[PDB]
Image (cartoon, grey):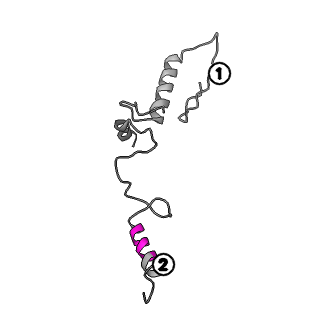
Amino acid sequence: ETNAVVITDLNPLYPRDRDYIYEGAAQIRLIKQTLQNTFPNVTEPVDIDSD
Amino acid sequence: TFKIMSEKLKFTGDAMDVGGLMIKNVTPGTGDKDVVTKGQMEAFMKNWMENKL
């Protein structure tokens, strides 16, 4: 499932259905590292003020 | 920058900063302390109290 993406580029239309999905744990690591790289500062991000 | 504005939580009328915005570079828009200097030049040097007044 690719690997080196840190620009919030996660392809969701290329998995597979009968072969190995022994990457769902690895997907979680890939998802987590993308989130950490984009915003490496998260303690209480209520600062949206949607209005 | 993000963390400080979080404690604000009241920015609804755009900026509404509690400071005085003590920085600016140029333009007849936002006014620095040079407005007073600009005013006296216009009032004295060229508009009201001209030379030989």
Q: Are marks 2 and 1 on the same chain?
A: no
Disc 2 packing (10 Å; few <14; some 14–19; many ≥20)? few
Mark 1 is surrounded, within 10 Å at the Cα level, by few (under 14), some (14 to 19) or many (20 or more) other residues, namely few
Return the residue at label 2: B47
Q: SS for tag 1?
A: loop
Q: Give the x, y percent position of residue B20.
A: 36, 53
Q: Chain of mark 1?
A: A
- Percent from the top left, x then y, of residue B30? 46, 59
Residue B26 image point, x, y percent: 48, 64
Please, which residue is most extreme toward the top here? A18
Residue placed most toward the observer, B21 or A11: B21
Comparing A23 with A38, the one in front is A38
What residue is drawn where x is 39% and y is 37%?
A: B10
For mark 2, name the chain: B
Give the residue drawn at x 52%, y 21%.
A27
Bounds of the magenta span? B35-42
Q: Quadrant of residue A16?
A: top right
**How far apart are labels 2 and 1 at the CA level?**
74 Å
Name the quadrant of the N terminus of chain B.
top left
Amino acid type, callout 1: Tyr
Q: Nearer the viewer, mark 2 or mark 1?
A: 2
Label 1 belongs to which residue? Answer: A14
**Which residue is painted at 35% across and 31% down in the image?**
A43
For the C terminus of chain B, which image quadrant? Answer: bottom left
Q: Secondary structure at mark 2?
A: helix
